[PDB]
Amino acid sequence: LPPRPWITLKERDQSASFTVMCYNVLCDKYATRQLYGYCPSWALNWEYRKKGIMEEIVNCDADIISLQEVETEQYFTLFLPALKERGYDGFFSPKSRAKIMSEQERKHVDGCAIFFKTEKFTLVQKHTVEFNQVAMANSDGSEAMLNRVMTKDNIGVAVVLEVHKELFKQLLIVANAHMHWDPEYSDVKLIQTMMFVSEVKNILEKASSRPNSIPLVLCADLNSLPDSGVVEYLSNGGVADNHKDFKELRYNECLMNFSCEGRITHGFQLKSAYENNLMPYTNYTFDFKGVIDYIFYSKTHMNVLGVLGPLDPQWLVENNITGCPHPHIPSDHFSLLTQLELHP
Ligand SMILES: NC[C@@H]1O[C@H](O[C@H]2[C@@H](O)[C@H](O[C@@H]3[C@@H](O)[C@H](N)C[C@H](N)[C@@H]3O[C@@H]3O[C@H](CN)[C@@H](O)[C@H](O)[C@H]3N)O[C@@H]2CO)[C@H](N)[C@@H](O)[C@@H]1O
Image 1 (cartoon, protein in one colour):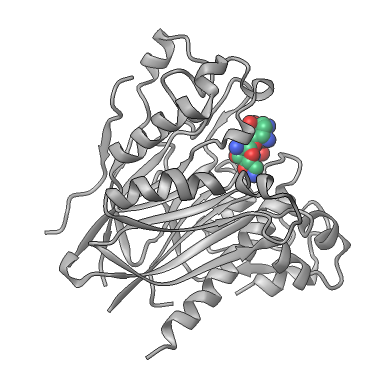
Image 2 (cartoon, rainbow, N blue to C red):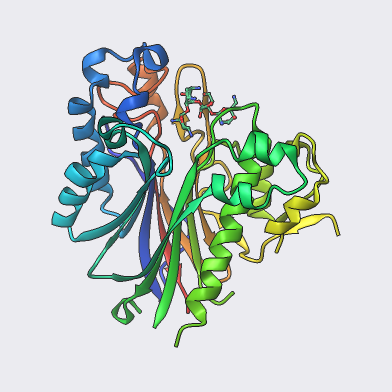
């Protein structure tokens, strides 16, 4: 397994630089022979894969790490203890807090974690966004909001961090979400994204009023290709309320609850670190290969200096690798890694 390359996109000036990782590790619960039958059982097994997962994370050595598919017990016994030793602290929330289940099932619920190096950042606030609660609260007048959106218990997490002056009070919000997966539910994915951005803006308003100005880095497994309403909404500061992906009700007035006519907008002016298909895919399986993971950043606060390019495709060809995971690749997603430059 050859080390991944690095694409330089812009030189360092000559004021704060830091790196961000985004990585869906593939949780044990979903690593089944049914879905990944082309991978031998011994290489699917968590006791085997978790080693490759930790190696990938250690090798990337990112200042900030956003993971998806982190199982609750594994956050507390594997990811946090190990990354504490590398100088990180972390924030984790699982999905399904409100769902009733046994002690044993609770250990295996997955969720999102953000880690940050404490020599560079200090935690100011931490937040969990429950898309099912936000949908329920904004569902008046929409059966679809209640039937299709509220019933999915996906989440995102966000932290407000202090960026230490030595790297140049400067604040930074890092947000990390994992959206619903089903290709037939583009509406849910889009609404979940608008709910998340909307709630992050509410978080940001309450980070400022404590004696628009705060940069955002948004990591996510959006389960959405670059041509989707989700990515258009994130990249262009808004989306039409009649966008095809809303699958009717399109023009529902309930969408405007997230919406700051006909356009649902946000003011974050985001850009994707990997735009212009610098990786041809982020999820790589036999049945599906495509870009569905993203690192977005406030383009008025930050430059992209570089990204970690894709695993060499001739290597996948020579080794006949048509899907992941694989004995040498421990997740069906490739990690994303970017170096950003923050100008206060
Ligand atoms: N062809 C339609 C496309 O599907 C893509 O996603 C693919 C994949 O991510 C997703 O399914 C994947 C596939 O392993 C297989 N279908 C089992 C399982 N559902 C898994 O979904 C899993 O669960 C999480 C739940 N939260 C997902 O967010 C996460 O990406 C994934 N680990 O559905 C697609 C099937 O591969 C993208 N959503 C988008 O490109 C478009 O919708």
